[PDB]
Amino acid sequence: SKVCIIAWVYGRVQGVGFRYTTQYEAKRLGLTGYAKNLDDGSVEVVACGEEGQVEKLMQWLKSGGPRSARVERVLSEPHHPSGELTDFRIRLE
Image 1 (cartoon, one colour):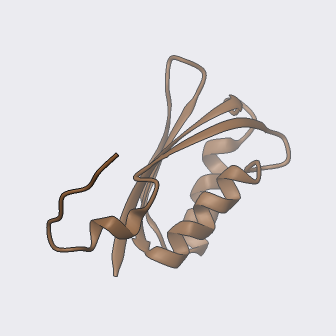
Image 2 (spheres, rainbow, N blue to C red):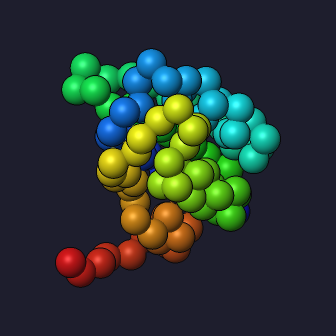
């Protein structure tokens, strides 16, 4: 079913078309959400849709996004988006 993630992408990610290309790939994957630049030199991505289509976006982001960019680190939440579909559970760290 429909999962959501939020990812923050650090590196050379602003002013190299990162937002515009995420839009393009997010559409092709039939995903909903948005992308936004932040004051700290990073880009936030919010994406919802089917869990396999979302994971294809997490892979594209992590594999570096567009070719004009140099992604150094990606922090997504949650790390296992499948935990969002389970009737309300408790979990250990």
